[PDB]
Length: 393
Ligand SMILES: Nc1nc2c(ncn2[C@@H]2O[C@H](COP(=O)(O)OP(=O)(O)OP(O)(O)=S)[C@@H](O)[C@H]2O)c(=O)[nH]1
Image: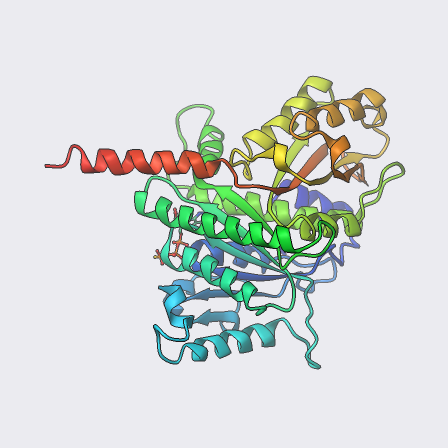
């Protein structure tokens, strides 16, 4: 099975009853980046050997997905992107539609036509052609009530390319508009057709990866940082899914129902901060949580102040005085409070226990408005395009 992180290693190593998750994701990747992500999700298995998430990958040609390793060929669906399905500016548009519907219907339904997932997790890299194109397509499909369940979009943001930036800003703007209409029409407590959008910033993940690993001068120079980024992003998502359902606490227990609400009710931008805490002291704890939020894999200058829900849990060792001290609890609370006053929004923070000697703090903020990365990207995009036009001879 896939053991994408030290935490997944420790879990399946000390827990042989990991046979269910909090929410049954139906994973669908689109474009190279998306496919790579979905291929990792397809690699996860329960203690009993069965597969965790049914997944499909999408792209234009068979060639694009030739190197997938966990998604069998049958599930590798092949067919700008918006034109094809557009019942007009592309003949037999319904053809592609019916095919998408059939493939989705055959992979996410049992024998009697019943959906076997709770929510669709669509992964894609913004900035590319098929990627952003699919993202934009997903929005129109949701507006057309295409999906039988809510959809969660996991999106990476580009950099270094003005053309990719512009494509990503167009999508984000379309996402934000969709969210505005959905937020006005649905009650703050109803399940939303667009559950959430989780953004990843390539520039941010690259810096994190290239700063670490290389305490000398040999950065290996051959390791694709993106592969490392994908592992970190996907294992975090998988981990937050299995923890609530497989781990409990003797104090504040976080349940799958809490996770489900957090992921489906807010309906806007959501982020995650995973902080491993081996050093059991207040300053190290605060510092690790803050780094995970402001300089972690899911950081994108989020508008934490606009969050409407939060959640999370510190998976801590049994019989560890540090994580049974009021000063610790107060530090965690006080630390999250610097991002968004918890007393003002729904949500809870649990402290599940696992059979290991270090703790991991998973902090989640949901229902936020446009990540400010939209702004820094629009600025960087303008600069690149300028130095581009400039210098030119
Ligand atoms: N985080 C992450 N980003 C990736 C990965 N592969 C590509 N990217 C980034 O994602 C963006 C789009 O990637 P890609 O998936 O190639 O787009 P696409 O539309 O599917 O490809 P095309 O149609 O332009 S060739 C680019 O900005 C690229 O730098 C990956 O495995 N992880």
